[PDB]
Length: 237
Ligand SMILES: *[B@@]1(C2=[C][C]=C([N]C([N])=[N])[C]=[C]2)O[C][C]([C][O])O1
Image (cartoon, rainbow, N blue to C red):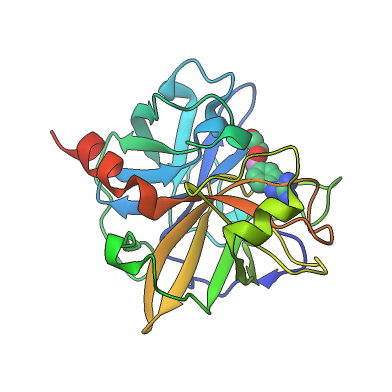
């Protein structure tokens, strides 16, 4: 996260840090708890990932330092990638992780509500992006979870900032016309939480952008509401 600040412990209880144990354990991507056994994240996050066995999901984490060899985690039973996904920039950058065990909800770890179709006309004026990603373009995974408030921008405006790209309605952008605040490497799969009527909603999934926090280059996120049907179908037994 560029231009953000340290999060308060338990401030984003749905945020998880997805680690890979290969070659050595390290933060790979962000993710959001949306169900007792389900993490919603970005598809492109599993590039070069041949098996879910090397994945470890940690919930209730503020600082990466909290994660040690003796720290409990959730194993991943299955990685579900949208069959239409090819690459982040083309869209469909969404994936579900079915955990091997169920998450016991608490103030430190609970699910975030998915947006409803009857909310696409809703004007989110309080949206935040979070994660342990880079603070700049050339940096490293941050220890403390960072947060940054960022305004959503119309798709028409976003398309203007991304000539050469096709910003579809299945994407949603957010950022400052002057930049300064935005997601970066490591924040992928992270949630773009928005607050309406004081009820947190998972509006987007951190996906891509040109550089990080550059002026006139809004972050591009997966427009979650466009995938509620997909999510329901993939989560049902
Ligand atoms: B992601 C990721 C997601 C979004 C952005 N945003 C910008 N401004 N470039 C950068 C990086 O984080 C992990 C990586 C793939 O493993 O992509």
